[PDB]
Image: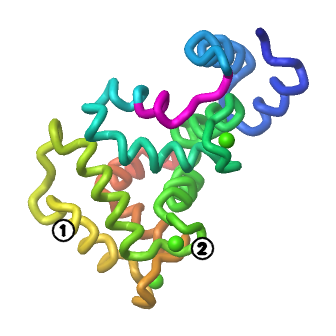
Amino acid sequence: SKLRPEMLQDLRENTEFSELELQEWYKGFLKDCPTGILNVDEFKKIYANFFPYGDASKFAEHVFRTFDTNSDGTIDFREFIIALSVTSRGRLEQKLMWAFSMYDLDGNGYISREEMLEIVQAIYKMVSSVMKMPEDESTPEKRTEKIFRQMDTNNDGKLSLEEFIRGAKSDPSIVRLLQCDPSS
Ligand SMILES: [Ca+2]
Ligand SMILES: [Ca+2]
Ligand SMILES: [Ca+2]
């Protein structure tokens, strides 16, 4: 019930957690999920702490699929800690790559319109009960309407990775973050 030296090392290489933190996380993850596999229903219960279960469920399924890199139906500790590390301590570039893999539902390497609207509908449903939204990006259709007409360079009905990454950096919260670049 400690990571084997060889696995510990492999995870220190593929994450931004220290040994102690990986050790602590493995203990916790096992203590909370004695099987060492986290399924969809379990994951939705994690999300339901933060937002009503029924509301968050469709977003929680989309995220679960992004964590589940081999797409077998469950998240093992490697898949979980890696995915957590990227999203919580990753570089902004690779955060947004990970978000792109999520938005791109068929995995053809292009965010289609009906792919975008799906995810945004789920994000809006999850938060509907607590967040009050802007006004112009304040229905999913309204929001999705903004994105493509701020992001679709050629207007090929699709968003490539490159159109997405750049587009997102105007997201107001990313505009806040860039003012903290330690390259003053
Ligand atoms: Ca899996
Ligand atoms: Ca696609
Ligand atoms: Ca395009």
Is the residue marked 2 within 8 Å of ligand 2, measured from its CB?
yes
Say whether residue 81 is magenta: no
Rate crowding at label 1 as few (under 14), some (14 to 19) or many (20 or more) other CA atoms within 10 Å: few
Q: What amino acid does circle 1 point to?
A: Lys
How has the structure been colored for display? rainbow
* Number of numbered discs visible in the structure rendering: 2
126 is higher (above) or lower (below) than 16: below
* Left or right, 33 with reference to 13: left
Q: In the rendered structure, which segment of residues is drawn in magenta?
A: 36-44
Q: Position of residue 53 (x, y in %)?
A: 30, 32
- Residue 106, how many percent across, how many down? 55, 68
Say which quarter of the image contains residue 162: bottom right
Residue under the point 43% across and 27% down:
46
Residue 108 has which mark? 2
Left or right of 169 on screen, residue 75: right
Q: Which residue is mark 1?
A: 142
Is residue 39 on the magenta stretch?
yes
